[PDB]
Amino acid sequence: LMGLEALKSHIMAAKAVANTMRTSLGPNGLDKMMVDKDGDVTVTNDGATILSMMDVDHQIAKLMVELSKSQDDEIGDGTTGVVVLAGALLEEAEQLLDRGIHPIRIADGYEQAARVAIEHLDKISDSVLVDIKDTEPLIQTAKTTLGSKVVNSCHRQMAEIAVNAVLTVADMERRDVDFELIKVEGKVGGRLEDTKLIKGVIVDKDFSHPQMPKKVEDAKIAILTCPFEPPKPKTKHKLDVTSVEDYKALQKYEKEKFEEMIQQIKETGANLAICQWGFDDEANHLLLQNNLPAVRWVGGPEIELIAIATGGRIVPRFSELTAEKLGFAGLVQEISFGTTKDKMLVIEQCKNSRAVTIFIRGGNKMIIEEAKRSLHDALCVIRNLIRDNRVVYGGGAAEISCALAVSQEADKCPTLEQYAMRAFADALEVIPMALSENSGMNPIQTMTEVRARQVKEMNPALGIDCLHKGTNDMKQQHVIETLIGKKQQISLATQMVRMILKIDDI
Amino acid sequence: DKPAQIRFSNISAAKAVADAIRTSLGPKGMDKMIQDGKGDVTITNDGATILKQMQVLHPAARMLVELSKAQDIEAGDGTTSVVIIAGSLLDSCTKLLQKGIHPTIISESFQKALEKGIEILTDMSRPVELSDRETLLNSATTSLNSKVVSQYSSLLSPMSVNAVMKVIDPATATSVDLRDIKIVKKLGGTIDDCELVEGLVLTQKVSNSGITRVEKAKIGLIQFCLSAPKTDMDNQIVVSDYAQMDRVLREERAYILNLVKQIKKTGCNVLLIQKSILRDALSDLALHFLNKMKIMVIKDIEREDIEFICKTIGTKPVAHIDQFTADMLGSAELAEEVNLNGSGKLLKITGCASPGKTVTIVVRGSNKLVIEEAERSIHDALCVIRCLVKKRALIAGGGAPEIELALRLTEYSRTLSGMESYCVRAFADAMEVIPSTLAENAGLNPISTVTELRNRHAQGEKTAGINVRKGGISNILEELVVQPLLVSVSALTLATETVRSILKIDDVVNT
Amino acid sequence: PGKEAVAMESYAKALRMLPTIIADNAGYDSADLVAQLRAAHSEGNTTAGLDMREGTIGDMAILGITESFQVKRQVLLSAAEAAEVILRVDNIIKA
Amino acid sequence: PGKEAVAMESYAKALRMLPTIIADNAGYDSADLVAQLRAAHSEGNTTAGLDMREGTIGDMAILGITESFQVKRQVLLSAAEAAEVILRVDNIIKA
Amino acid sequence: TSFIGAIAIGDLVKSTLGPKGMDKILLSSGRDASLMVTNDGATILKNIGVDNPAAKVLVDMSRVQDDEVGDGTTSVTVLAAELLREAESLIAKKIHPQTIIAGWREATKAAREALLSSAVDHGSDEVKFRQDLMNIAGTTLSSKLLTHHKDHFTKLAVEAVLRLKGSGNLEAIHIIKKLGGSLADSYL
Amino acid sequence: ELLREAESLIAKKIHPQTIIAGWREATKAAREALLSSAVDHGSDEVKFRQDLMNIAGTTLSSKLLTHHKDHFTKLAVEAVLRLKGSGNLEAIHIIKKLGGSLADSYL
Amino acid sequence: SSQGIPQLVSNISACQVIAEAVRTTLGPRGMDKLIVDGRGKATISNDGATILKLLDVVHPAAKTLVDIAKSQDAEVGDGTTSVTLLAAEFLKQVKPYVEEGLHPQIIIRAFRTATQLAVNKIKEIAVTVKKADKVEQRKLLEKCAMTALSSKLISQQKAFFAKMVVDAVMMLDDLLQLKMIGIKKVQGGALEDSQLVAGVAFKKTFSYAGFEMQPKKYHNPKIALLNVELELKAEKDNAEIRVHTVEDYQAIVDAEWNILYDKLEKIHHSGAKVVLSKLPIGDVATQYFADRDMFCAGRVPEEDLKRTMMACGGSIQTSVNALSADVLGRCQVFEETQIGGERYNFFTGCPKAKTCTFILRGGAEQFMEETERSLHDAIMIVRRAIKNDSVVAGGGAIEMELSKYLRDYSRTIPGKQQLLIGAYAKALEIIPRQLCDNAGFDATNILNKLRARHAQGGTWYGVDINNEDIADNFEAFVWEPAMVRINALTAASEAACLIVSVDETIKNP
């Protein structure tokens, strides 16, 4: 099969993946089941995973997932919308090619309609930005993340932690700021409300040193990796002493290595000390008698991340015990590891912004992974909102506003691209179409109702209801999505159509 | 399940009929060979001559045939545009039911689209006033020059204008009766001799001894017995001689004069001959006696002529002799048999009183096909002028109405709300097949041509259409092709009526 | 109002199926028995139930038959949320 | 109380299906309309009806769309007796 | 036997039910040139060829008392068919038929009592009679296409029937089938 | 049963998310009614003793055992009354021993 | 197969099939093809040379056509599609005549004389403006690249793109594969501004603290070309030591890293003064390199190494060996400039400036990919054009000029060769036809008026892909080199005549 018939079958396969993804749109998205090679199962409506985890034995479907992945971090929530919009564009292009239009012509028509839709998106702008006072507007924007997924209590704390982390990690806020370094961490355990923002790194610690000062105002930190007690490079070490007084000589050597070095280190302004491996608690008793708060069991990647956080690089031997080599913290504080049953000491490094991370807890592995994806999406949307302060009303409102714009613009040209832009219009219409399909209300009735509301009254903030608030205006609903986010979604959809609309593959 | 499936099947049959007919559209046209039981050929550029002889099985095909027949009897031309609109609307319906929206909403939305489309077509058209001869001749020449009957429609257009002026004053907007203006043939002849005949042309008479012409003719409407009935056999007894049948023979010879004396007290001049299954008998041996004292017999009258003469000269229908009173008599000005430019025995009635001013046109020609082509030319000329006079304000053709109507109907669907909005949008964006069909039959890229027409109708002239006689999109030439506004009105209204009826139809059932 | 009425009525009848299943496993005239119990609650008897030792309806306070509140509440909520999480998925993707 | 409670509910659902068909033939959302009508005149408000002219809940008292009592009673009784006649035959034989 | 026929007749009548329904087309056998389109389900039931004896006895049991009252056919047939389908579901759920008969007898008694309670009297007042008669005519004359002609039927029928004031003249009323002028106006 | 009726409703062309919303509302109402209708045996001693006895006996009757349910339940409530409210699953020491009869069980 | 016509028509069909692998990829906006490798790798390339290189061809006729295509790719690279389409269409238009039974040697000499005449006509009608020294001609090459780039339709920054690319290619760049002079694309930022990199360097550095205080502006850094790295957890010693004191265990932790510390110390003291590594490097390693007053770049691509070979004049080190500055490359410019969000480290200015690459930043993805192809094509065409003696109007125009000339000569030459030359001329029409079809499928509608106005009078008019209308392909600054067109037409003719000269295919399995 070659030519237009091969492209017809290819559009059929693209529709096969697209309508499968269709039901997952929006906050009210219907979930999907994934069973993997490992045999595990998970319920999830987030598009990014159910493309990445999904595999389809067709090359164009592989390009679908690859091109969605390429803008994964760039567009978090859109992972569903871009794919469904590309699918609708291909479904309309099916009819367009059945009418005989050559594929690059409709591709360029889609590009022209993309330009028109982008310029129309420019016309809607909100979200005045000032970093200190933005807290309330930004948590109202993160209300979209809060009210959608399983967070029924809609914790304002997670919205606040995300917005404060993103606003603090870069002091300059005008444009294209370096929000690449931040990341979120989490593990199964306590409630979802068990969260804490750190201007540094949280370490993992064993429950020795029980009542020791886990909180110290250490401006500087001892990053001494030398073994205070016999080391273990995957290889254990041995002990051999002639008598109990020989072991007491070993004790006084240990006392030299503890009091003398740590007196020097405190002279350099550090009390907290790292150890690369722990051996036994009777050696820890000397450290307790020295009132030492210390942590250990840091892995290779763990200790390297500690180094990048504290700016100091590891000290393996005695001769390198100087102030300059050890890493800085400025402050250290201690916070419960779980809810209350276990405790953790956390090292902030506030004097440098190069390390800010978010810790979250969850009552289940499904709960923790859902929190991972939800907080990643919230981080993405807040990042993309503060990168470009302009915003547009979501809930399908922006897509149908662009639908009106490009459909009314379709009469502006004499060339074949007119049907291409009309196809773009009734394909942008799919977002409320499918967003009501996966919701309860009748798709076309509500879609055309809000579409005509945008004509009887000029405000483009009208969209379909997705949380049953009883109102079709999205301004009070505040289901809002970043303007540059919408621009990226539409542009990626147009490119994603183009990259398989001009294909006559083997 | 079943209702959706049966509606899909009905739509498929209607669309198959329409798309088989689609190629043959408009003056350019392209024909098919008809799939018939005899195996002959057709070179008929038009579209009507396929449906009128189409072997139709599915009821959708039959209903589209009724569609075409209704369009033809209403306004004549457009008989293919109507069916192609029907097919395109059914294709849009296929799309809409593929998405699953309900048929009743389809019907209501198409009714709304029809109303707004009629408003739009009435709006943009040129409000030409039809009250005097110059306007009538302008409309006639614009209607005739755009078709292939122009060569001979020229001489007959003023005469058709005269006929329609006889029927009514054009200030009266009521439609003239197409059937009232009858068309007749006098065998053979030239072309120019086709002339208006005020009154009626009548069938040929028998001329034993009857007068050829009579001033102030006293026309009688006779349908009753002629003789003592030869009821069942030529002889009732032994056939050695007609001993007793001589009685009924001389009773014929007596009843002929009895009825002629019953006539002369009224004065019946002519005799329309009904067939021998209604009459007792008809033969020269009595028709001569009727003729010689002024009762001229005219051969083989038919019911349409009887109705026409009743409507014209006021002679009440007759079934018996006793009503020979003046109710069955008419008093014309003159009745003559005229044989100029080739002999012909067709009688003419002139100047008789009439409530309705019925008028007929006699058709002449060196060949029978020429006579019948002149008849169909005058027929469609009367159709177009009547559908203009009853609705005024003719419209430019050539897909321009379809482009302009689709554009404003798409924006109407834009401003419209509810489920019906997308239905009207689909109606508009599928109705544009007619200009696409003209582009296909003109050689241009159909889709690019439709886009160019839609763009030119936007932000500019709304009368621009596809020109069939010069080529391509044109706006500067106003006289691209023009049809009476009723052509498009009837097309849209009948198409939408049948489409919404098809939508209303469910679960076909054999009796 | 709304389409939710039929959905929750069907949920109620699915709940009704549970004692219907209990009676069916008991061999009694399960449909008639659950109809009788439904009528008893409709006329109003918050303590009316099924006597499992011998099939008939009875005011369950006198009989002393009962179950702990916590287990019943948790069964209802957990079954509801499990059916919800199953239903919220339309298709399964396999590899 | 009897097992015919299920049959009574079935009768109620079948009678409820008639306005459902009225809505379906008119193209409106049948399930939503009938459920919201059930709510609209189950909470009292006995005069509430389904306005087919626009597909919305309609207080039928002032709209004036009314049906004569005799035809409604006759159709109810005739449907009942015809359904009884058709139902009460279980097997058929032919010559 | 199972009620496939009794629900098949109901399903083929269903889409015609009430105004804004769906039309049916009835055509003669033998592929002759004759067909007609109709909306009134009574016409389909009259023209239907009942090959199923259950459907035949159902339509016969309707005809004895459905065309008498008028317009009940499209309601009685569909309601009976839906009842038979629901009862087929019930007997699939092992509910004995006689239980269903008793339940439906009592339920119909209750429904008729509720209908009588909800029925509102409109006697003794002329203006209430006028408005009620126009409303009932409009609901019964819910078949013609032209809405102004709908009103024409409503007014003509109401004024023809009200002028009685006494015992029925339905035995004496007639509607002459003579063809006249415009297809949108009526006369008495 | 819920999933059976859910598939039946999907056949009736009722969308899954409407089913979820209606089901959640129904569970809210049912849980509220159950809580408002459940009976707190409350502040009593002898009546509470009888209530503890029979509720424990019937809850243990849900298992296969039918003979010695009462003895185990009485022993358990004796332990819980030694708790006086301080619920302790580990107050009872649970040793196992193969052989013998169910009547040979001892606390 | 069978001798003569029955096998030659099979060769015709095979050449048509191999054309279908290229037929729709002629124009710059032509359809792209996804070709799947047997390994399960999906690759996308809209240029026929790469497609045929990835595509395995088995049929001998397709084998010969692809071999000629590869020879042309070694000649120019874009002419692969043109020569394949010409060969296929020549065979298609002789198919009715060869099926009629005329001997193929006739068409061999017919094509020979027709293409010799076509070469004569090309050399006669080709014109030169060259004279590139003056600023007017610099901006003439600028507008040529602008017309090649016209998909962007940007404002004056369109001309800025053109000026930057023409300057980068004109600075001491000889005719070569052009791979070292490539481009990169960056998110964010204004498309009006981007970096004219005077060489090539590393895509995006890491978040290490050594980056922020990295020593910008090396005056003349000697470079180290490494591949082996130092990183965490990679290596360790399984030593066991009995306790003697507390000062002894540091022998084990010493042995874990001492060889690595000495290795880094010596390889940095080798004589180089900035070091590159293809594999990831540790932040702790970066800090010890800062202790060496030095910086390291890890995870560098191999194309960085190759561009270092051809431009920086360096040599691979690949390990701690070669503790000498002799084998080390040199640079004249170094810095780091975070291009928007792109944390690009720069080390540029080389003994050979063959690469002076550019990096794009326009805040998109869909535009700058076709932009990469467009700049590739423009910078290619300028360098091939300057080498050749003369240039001729391309983009479907000169194909029509030759078609008209050969039709006129065919219709006047006697003998059976004239039908064959007419078939050749009609087959030469394929390039305008495919340029139109791949652009708007309106091939006939524009082709008719094109041929008519071309026959109206002597002009270089052809098809313009930008507006689907006839444009002055010459003086619209869309061109094809005359010598390259001679090579393409002659190679296509030789391929066609060779493949239609063969009757039998011989097998000896």
Image: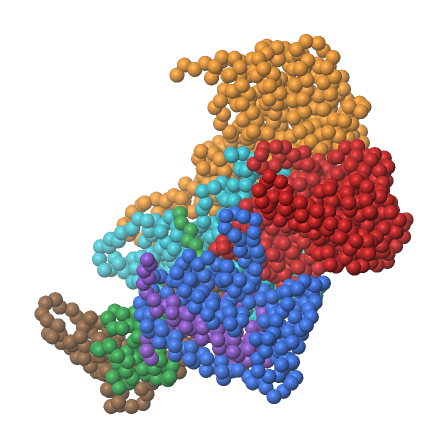
Chain colours: A cyan, B red, C green, D purple, E blue, F brown, G orange
Q: Position of residue B502 (x, y in %)?
A: 59, 54
The x and y percentages for residue A290 are: 37, 66
Q: Residue B125, position in %: x, y?
A: 80, 53
Tell me if B58 is positioned left or right of G467 in this view: left
Q: How many numbered circles are shown?
A: 0
Viewer-side residue, G46 vs A263: G46
**Horizontal placement of B401 versus C37: left or right?**
right
Which residue is rendered at x = 40% and y = 69% of the image?
D83
E43 displayed left or right of A103: left
Residue F68 locus on image (x, y percent): 16, 77
Q: Nearer the viewer, residue B151 or G194?
A: B151
Image height of A221 relative to B57, above or below: below
In which quadrant of the rendered view does residue B346 lie?
A: top right
Q: Is residue B479 above or below residue C90?
A: above
Residue depicted at 32% across the width and 63% down the height: D91
Q: Is residue G323 left or right of residue G390?
A: left
Q: Nearer the viewer, residue G395 or A88?
A: A88
Residue most extreme to the left: F100
Residue D19 visible: no
Please name whichever residue, A294 or A60, is drawn nearer the observer in this view of the structure. A60
**Taking the image as drawn, is residue E187 in sight?**
yes
Q: Residue at x 63, y 30 (%)?
A: G26
Which residue corresponds to the image point at 63% horizontal and 54% vertical from the top-left?
B498
